[PDB]
Amino acid sequence: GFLELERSSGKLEWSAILQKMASDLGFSKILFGLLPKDSQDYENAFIVGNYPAAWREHYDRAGYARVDPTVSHCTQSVLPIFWEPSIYQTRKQHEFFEEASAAGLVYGLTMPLHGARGELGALSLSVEAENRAEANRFMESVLPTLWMLKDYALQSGAGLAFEHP
Amino acid sequence: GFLELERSSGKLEWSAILQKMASDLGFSKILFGLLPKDSQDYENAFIVGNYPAAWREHYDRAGYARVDPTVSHCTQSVLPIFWEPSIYQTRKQHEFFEEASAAGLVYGLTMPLHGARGELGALSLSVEAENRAEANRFMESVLPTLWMLKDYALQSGAGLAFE
Ligand SMILES: COCOc1c(Br)cc(Br)cc1CNC(=O)c1ccccc1[N+](=O)[O-]
Ligand SMILES: COCOc1c(Br)cc(Br)cc1CNC(=O)c1ccccc1[N+](=O)[O-]
Image (cartoon, rainbow over all chains, first blue to last red; front, side, top):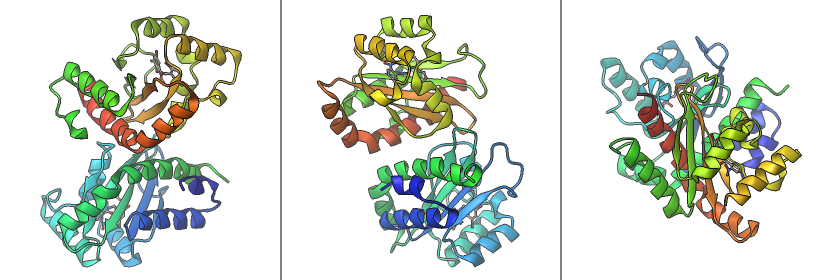
C-alpha cells in the first residue's frame, strides 16, 4: 500500500493518500510538516493534512511552535512522543493542552522526521477514544505499521515538497 | 522491550542486547555504524556488531565504503535497501557481492540511520538462508519489528557514542 505515496502526482493526491492510510490505522486527524535543512523560520515549510483550519490558524497566531512540547522533542529524537499533559510543564503548555483538547485533539502522538538530506519535520496523528488507556491500546496496536508509514511519508514527501517539478 | 537498549549500562551491554534482539528476530549477523554530523572520514566512527573480523578487515583494506552500494543509498534515503542482484550494477559491485558471500554474508538488508543531530549511519543485518525466496519470506515477516528496532538503536546508540 505504501507505493501509492511515491506513485501519486501532486500535493493534493499525496495528502489524500496519506490521510486515508492514517485513517485506516485508526487516526482521524493528521498533520505532516517538513522543513528544509537548517531552516530558521517556517516560511519554507511544507505542511499538509486535515487538522481543522481554526486550530491551524490559532496555533500559528499564538506562537505555539515555541510552546508545544513535541517541537523541541523532534529536534532531539527520532522516537515518537505521545501527547500527554506530563510533557506539559509550564503555564502556556497547560493553555496549549486545554486549547488542543477543546479543538478535539486530545490523544495522539508526534513522530519526528529526520530526512537523509537534513530535512526536519513531524507526522502528528490524533486518535479518537473514550479515554487515554483506550487511545494507548489503539496506538500500540498499529505502531509497527505507523513506523514504516512515517518513513515512507518522509522519503516521498521530501521529494514532493522540495524536489519534484 | 525496545527501551532495553536505552536502559543498557554501556557499550558492552548495549552491543550484547542489540545482537541478541537481532538474533531472536532471526539475524545471526549485524553491524551498527554511526558517524557524527558532517564527518570527513571514519576516524570518529562508532561501529558495533558481530560481522566476522576477517570481513571487517577486508572491507576496510579494500576501501569498500566506496564500492558497497548501500553506502550511497544511505546518504539518499531513509528506506531500507535489500541485498538483491539489482543493487550490484558494476563488476566492482559484483565482486563486492561475491566477497561478502564468500564471507558468509549473502542475504540481508541495510537500514539507513539519520539522527536528530545530523548523525549518519546504517544498521545492516544478514540472514542465513538456502535461497532468496526463503530469505525474502523471513524478512517480510520481521520487517515491521526491524523498522522500529533501527530507530531505537539509533537514538540509544547516538547517546552512547557521542556523549
Ligand atoms: C512538531 O512541530 C509542530 O507541528 C505542528 C504545527 Br507546525 C501545527 C500544529 Br496545529 C500542530 C503541530 C504539531 N503538534 C501537534 O499536533 C500536537 C501535539 C500535542 C498535542 C496536541 C497537538 N495538536 O496540535 O493538536
Ligand atoms: C553502510 O555503511 C557502510 O557500513 C559497513 C561497514 Br563501515 C563495514 C562493513 Br564490513 C559493512 C558495512 C555495511 N554493508 C553491508 O553490511 C553489506 C551490504 C550489502 C551486501 C553485503 C554487506 N556486507 O557487508 O556483508
